[PDB]
Amino acid sequence: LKQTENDLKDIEARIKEKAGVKESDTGLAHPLQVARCTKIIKGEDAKYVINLKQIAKFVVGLGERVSPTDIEEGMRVGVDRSKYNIELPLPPRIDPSVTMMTVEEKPDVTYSDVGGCKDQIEKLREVVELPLLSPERFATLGIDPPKGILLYGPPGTGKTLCARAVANRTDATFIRVIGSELVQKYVGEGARMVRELFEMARTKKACIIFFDEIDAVGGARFDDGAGGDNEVQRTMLELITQLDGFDPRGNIKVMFATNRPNTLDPALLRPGRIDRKVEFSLPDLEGRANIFRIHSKSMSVERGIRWELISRLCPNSTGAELRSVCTEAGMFAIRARRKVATEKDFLKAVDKVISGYKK
Amino acid sequence: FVSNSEILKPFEKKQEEEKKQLEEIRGNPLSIGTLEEIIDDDHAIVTSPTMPDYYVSILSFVDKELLEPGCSVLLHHKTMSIVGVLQDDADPMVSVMKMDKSPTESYSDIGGLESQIQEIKESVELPLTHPELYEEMGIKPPKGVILYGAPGTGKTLLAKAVANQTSATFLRIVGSELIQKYLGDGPRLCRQIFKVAGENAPSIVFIDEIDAIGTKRYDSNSGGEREIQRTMLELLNQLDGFDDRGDVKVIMATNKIETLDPALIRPGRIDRKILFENPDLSTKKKILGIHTSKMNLSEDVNLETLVTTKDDLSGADIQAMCTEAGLLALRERRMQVTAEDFKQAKERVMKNKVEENLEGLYL
Amino acid sequence: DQVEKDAEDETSSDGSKSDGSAATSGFEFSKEDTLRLCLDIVPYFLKHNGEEDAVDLLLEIESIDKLPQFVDENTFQRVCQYMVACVPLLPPPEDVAFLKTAYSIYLSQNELTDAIALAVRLGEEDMIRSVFDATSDPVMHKQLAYILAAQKTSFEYEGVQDIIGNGKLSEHFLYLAKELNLTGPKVPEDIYKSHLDNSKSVFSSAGLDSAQQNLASSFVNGFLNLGYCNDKLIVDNDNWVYKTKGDGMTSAVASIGSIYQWNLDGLQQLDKYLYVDEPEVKAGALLGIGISASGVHDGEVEPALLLLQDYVTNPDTKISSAAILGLGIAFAGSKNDEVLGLLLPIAASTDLPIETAAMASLALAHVFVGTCNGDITTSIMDNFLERTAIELKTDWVRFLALALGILYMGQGEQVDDVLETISAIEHPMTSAIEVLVGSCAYTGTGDVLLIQDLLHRLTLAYAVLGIALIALGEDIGKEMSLRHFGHLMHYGNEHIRRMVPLAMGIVSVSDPQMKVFDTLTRFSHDADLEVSMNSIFAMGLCGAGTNNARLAQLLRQLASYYSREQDALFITRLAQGLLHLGKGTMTMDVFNDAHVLNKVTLASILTTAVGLVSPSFMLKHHQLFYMLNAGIRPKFILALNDEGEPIKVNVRVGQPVLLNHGERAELETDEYISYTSHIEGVVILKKNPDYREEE
């Protein structure tokens, strides 16, 4: 078997070059990243003969046919950007985007840096925890859960761990799709990933579809209207057709996170789709105490320090600056040459934050 | 030559069976490209820079685990079949790529900056040269460092001096090259910076002179751009996703941090803010000692004589002032500056340069 | 140009003690007209005190005869400071042999600073003792004794130890009876043994059940508990001892010897299994005593190791195998004709069921290394070619030649006995030995010829030994060596493949590098399964003394091995026990601040290369895994007052917050002023006469 794989190049590799190249290139033309055909006469029924390049575009007439598995030959049959007639059932859905979407069922995150966010948790208790726990209560209430929940606050703070904190109490599926790869103007990139989210959400009830940085997606941008691309043009339709149009509410929920509401299409901003807006505020002294005691387990600290004092001397600060206090405390300990962080080490770390921020 | 003839030469000469014909049957020509997708069915998609994108097959050379999409591989010209795999460094990443080895600057040549040396050392050199100090404390060392100053002194001497002691390759990325004025080049070029330093990590990322991506403003006008807003967000995800013991650092220096995105700031990732300070008289004594080792000075003039008159010069113009001090001696036809030359040379320097006068005559 | 051409062809080293010879006999060096050129620049820099730039002229043209002429009058102090920062490397090439000519002119004077430089670099037997002749202060000789114990080399065996170690009254000796036990790891190792009681950490050791799997537990018992006394496993539950038989019983008591190591007496502790019934129980007993005796030679108040020399020759099978290996480790540094006379007939006939000479070839190499003997290589040379008595198998014939890679160190012109064995029977390892035996003739390394000769071999497995020596003392040969090491990992035999990670792993504590760590991907899985088993043991030695830190990249290569089967448990645990070796916190130091190595530790390095056959093919005995205790250096730093007596002294702390006598520390710089030959680690400080202080 070891020497068997070596001599197959003299036998098997002869047909593989003809069947994998010559058969695909026949007529001056499985994952498909490219498809084309040139001067092909077939037959009306599964004829294809479509050039996916913007040069020399082709269509298909004579009725309508649906062949989602194999249209004619497979292979060089494709769609890519522009829709042509009956070619829709075979889209090129292959893409190494698996590093973008992160699917986590029932996250175990409760409070890490979100300590003191219970004010925002109560905002997410009625519109998220309630429909994902006892959805039958809305039949007696008569109202409806919001189709979507919008997140707002300081950039890069409170829009990450706060979404997974409510997902634990709901025992739901948290699917985070980073909008950074959807920034592309490539035709069909945005509408394809959004459509697949609602398909997997119909299989398992009580799931949470999260869109990271909706400002990177939005309902409209400069390359949508001014450009000839349908990117984000058909993507908003997937949110209108699936979420509000057909798919239920308590079973399939959608959550957005933005740095400002004015960057979203008012069509999605109007009530009926995006209703509640969650704003991240500054935690209180009780919130800072619960976060410091959790970080004190990972970092070496003195057994005699008291966080009820130094944290009180610091005013209300963002959750990102609270992790900085624990990291900067060890920096002064290295200068002081101590295996742990004494009470004087945390004092110099807070004063460094007060003098450089004043928030 | 003698060893290779009696060792490596008979290895290839005695036994020739395979590895010679592997590059034959598939094809002789070579056209470099990038793998779009890899599967177990022995078929893939390759695209050359000339865009002859086709659908071809695969023959067994390296296992499918070694083949990854997004890297340059060994291909064929006409049939475009995969004949092997190559190194990914041939893929263009950033328009301006500068890799410098063995930087010349060090802590001894930058003068009296030891006040700022301990700051840049703790956030860069200390976790690299002492990873156990941050590990026992259970904390993560700061990856980023904020610097203030002028190019050639503040934003230059501090960056190159650390790479010498850390024994890391100097990697410079121009701040304006992060934004190519094309949508999608922002997140693409930022991920490729951490990719070169993400294998063996024998380097440190350096970025200097950012007048552009540091300020996105509110819009695509007034110096900002819309592509900057979404680029600084992906750099945050690449900063938090990047995890090591500190072998690679990201050092960016700009004029003002007030226009930066609070997301990319991310307190606790960047714990270091180094503001340019006015050095004292002891700084000049360290810069003079370097050049006075070559240029000979008179016995009546010591390091305390030249440091007497110093007006708002840190480290840069001490060499420029000594340049005129050696140029005036050429007029007197002598190779050794003596006491008569020091007096006439320093007067031509300190005078007739700064027109604005900061003076206490407001009364 | 004449010196560079004459240095390429010579039968001797660089430098000479004759300043009046024209070098016209034999190989010609200096010409007739060049005799006046040697004295030309001497008087000019003599009056102006320009020896700083005057030696730099000698460093470029490599003239050894000018240096003694510059010493006449005026300042003998400042000329010593310019010698330290200039002589070793002025140019791209490095020549350290210029200090040999200084011993003649400074013989009656020397200097406080000069005596430091004459005891380093070459380190001739007469040059090392020159520091004691100039300084008459007995306090200064105390600090020098801690350095001499670390250096070993010239003065180790009888004639200093066991003789002067009992005390002597004179001007140029001044060796106290306490300085014998205190400098070497004898008294301090017992006090340090008590500090590890409160410093102990969580232990994973256990006894398990069956003797087949007790080999995996015995590996965790001995190495993890090294330096710490444990009476729970050794006394109460013998299931991990008594149930093991054969080679398993030898390694079982071998685990006990490392537990009781660094104690005042390692004999009476093991007397339980010393004499019972069978030689199998008696085997590991003598093996553990020699392991527990590592670091001590003549004992403290009694020559305890002198009476153990009668256990070398035994007709029993299992005893003689574990006696030669155990006692061979403890007898290092002590040269005795009785130990030599016993080991010659054992390694001659190589009788397997009786003599067990597999470890006898390495016994002579681990003991007498650093000494001068021409008879030790003569008896092996005659037995190598003729194969006297019952010697048959060619492997045992090669095992002798592999053991011959040690004895010739420091022997000078006596290396010819090794060349006769290479020309007798051709071996793959002996091909590169004939090149590196010349380094002993030049009394050092770093020569342009030696560097060029190594390039002739590379552009085979043994030739990389001298490459790593130059890489540590020179950065020019170190940068290129990293490029050559990548292309030398592909070869027919596996010898060169396993030497790459081991050479960088011993020095990984001083200068760790992640480039060699990622090359272990192909080293873990290559062809044979014996490589994968030895790879885990090799990665463990690379990680001994340091927990994670830069070794996290090395840990990624270890993450590929977790658990497979019952027999694979001991295979995967090889690295785990070595990471926790010495309770996880320790150091391995083969060097010092004198820019010289320890021939006793270097012998243990080459001994494990020739040894460690049990994890490799053709498993012999399970005792081969404990061979690492021969090269383990104890980690401690003494805090001493101006009188050299143990006391609590407040200074810069080491690696443990309170420094005292026998406290664990290492790798710490010292900027404080000392008496003579300032050195890190153990140091005796003082204070200027303006104030009375211990700092």
Image: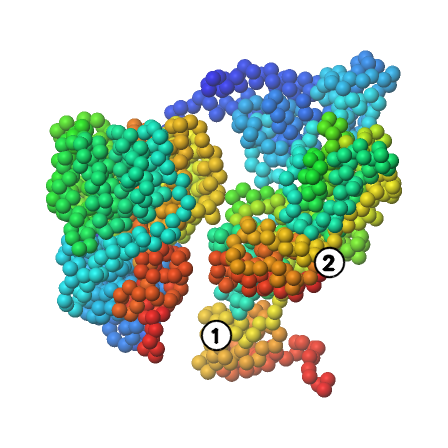
Answer whether residue C461 is visible to the viewer in this image: no
Which residue is pictured at 43% across the width and 39% down the height? C486
Q: Position of residue B318 (x, y in %)?
A: 56, 72
Q: Quadrant for the N terminus of chain C, please.
A: bottom left
Callout 1: chain: B
Answer whether residue C614 is visible to the viewer in this image: yes
Q: Quadrant for the C terminus of chain C, please.
A: bottom left
Residue A239, by quadrant, is top right
Q: Which of B161/C152 is in front?
A: C152
The residue type indicated by label 2 comes to Thr
User: How far separated are the C-alphas under marks 2 and 1?
Assistant: 52 Å
Q: Secondary structure at mark 1?
A: loop
The residue type indicated by label 1 comes to Met
State yes or no: discs 2 and 1 in contact (Cβ < 8 Å).
Answer: no
Horizontally, residue B353 falls left or right of residue C168, namely right
Location of residue A287 with respect to B53 vertically, above or below: below
Q: Which mark is residue B259?
A: 2
Which residue is pictured at 71% across the width and 85% down the height? B361
Q: Which of A39/A122 is in front?
A: A122
Callout 2: chain: B
Which residue is the extreme one toward the top? A43
Q: Position of residue C23 (x, y in %)?
A: 20, 57
